[PDB]
Length: 133
Ligand SMILES: Cc1cc2c(cc1C(=O)O)C(C)(C)CCCC2
Image (cartoon, rainbow, N blue to C red):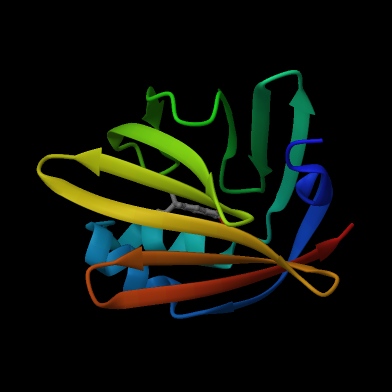
């Protein structure tokens, strides 16, 4: 019953500051424009100790599977090759990505009937809000 309140299919309903977050990460103009238009569904499931998170949109379909605390290599939707570790910290899923001496953190939390995603790169934060699909 690890992550039960996260499991399901979620749809993006609002975004703030995502273009600025992508700029801080190093995403180029064309990819920012198309990515910023995306309205993903996020699908989260658990089978034993393995968590799977899928993001599906017209921009890209991605999938990661992982065990908490156990690093993995990830190819991001913007084509970064990163080393990722995802942990649970006080009920929040915390996803750290490292690449080229840089780091970004993506936090997922349940708030009311929403799943709120905060993406942070240095001083720039983007908030993406999801509801059940
Ligand atoms: C649509 C989308 C695009 C991108 C991302 C996430 C999402 C998403 O909504 O999950 C990264 C987290 C890889 C950030 C860089 C730009 C590419």
